[PDB]
Amino acid sequence: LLKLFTTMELMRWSTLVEDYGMELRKGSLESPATDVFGSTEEGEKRWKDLKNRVVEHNIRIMAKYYTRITMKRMAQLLDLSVDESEAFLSNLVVNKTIFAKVDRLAGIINFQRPKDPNNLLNDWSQKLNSLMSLVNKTTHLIAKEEMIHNLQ
Amino acid sequence: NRHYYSITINYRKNELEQKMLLNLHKKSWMEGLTLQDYSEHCKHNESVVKEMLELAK
């Protein structure tokens, strides 16, 4: 649960293989894992849908970051094919990846770098940067000016 | 006005009232560090006032 909680480091599911396997083996707790695999196809749908759901979820986590993990490298670190990464992109176009950048030339993607209107976006960055510099500059200024009063 | 008259009124203002009330009122129309709301409207020239520029046209 805490690994599914937030800020998911891209982790190996082979580490989850022994977790789910002994999660079938032990009858100490959560005995109906064999009931999760109860139907011949349904637990397989839960399983491929499960690996699918986390392998989309972590992409939505690193999609917050603009750090550009360069998905041709990511498909190599994931040890999975880029064709099912195109299938992952078919899950992304219905998962609304619609604000992104792909390449005919490269295979590296960008989740950002919009058209960037300077009357909107660099407007906004310049606004909160300048203003927060001004008023954060304002407060501890007079506050430390009150702190030096107590040394007298 | 019969049986009932009036008297003139003048004032007095010393320089502490003058400059205290004056910088009090200019400061009541100015900002704290005073550089604060400048870039705000400089960049509302890019966000808001462009609409008022088109409506002006």
Image (tube, helix red, strand yellow):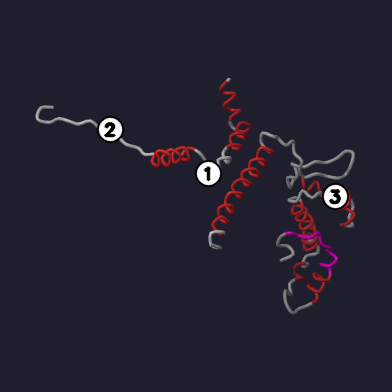
Who's the residue at 74% across and 79% down the image? A28
User: Which contiguous range is marked in magenta?
Assistant: A7-17
Per the image, the residue denoted by label 2 is: B10
Q: Main secondary structure of the magenta part?
A: loop
Q: Amino acid at mark 3?
A: Met
Dot 2 falls on which chain?
Answer: B
Secondary structure beneath disc 1? loop
Q: In the drawing, what numbered circle is on residue B32?
A: 1
Question: Residue A13, how many percent across, how many down?
Answer: 83, 63
- Membership of A42 in magenta stretch: no
Q: Amino acid at mark 2?
A: Asn
- At label 3, counting other C-alpha atoms closer than 10 Å, the crowd grade (few under 14, some 14-19, many 20 or more) is some
Compute the Cα span from label 2 to label 1: 34 Å
Along the viewing direction, whichever of A130 and A30 lies nearer the viewer: A130
Along the viewing direction, whichever of A41 and A100 lies nearer the viewer: A100
Marks 3 and 2: in contact by CB < 8 Å? no
Q: Are marks 2 and 1 on the same chain?
A: yes
Question: Residue B47, how many percent across, how many down?
Answer: 62, 33
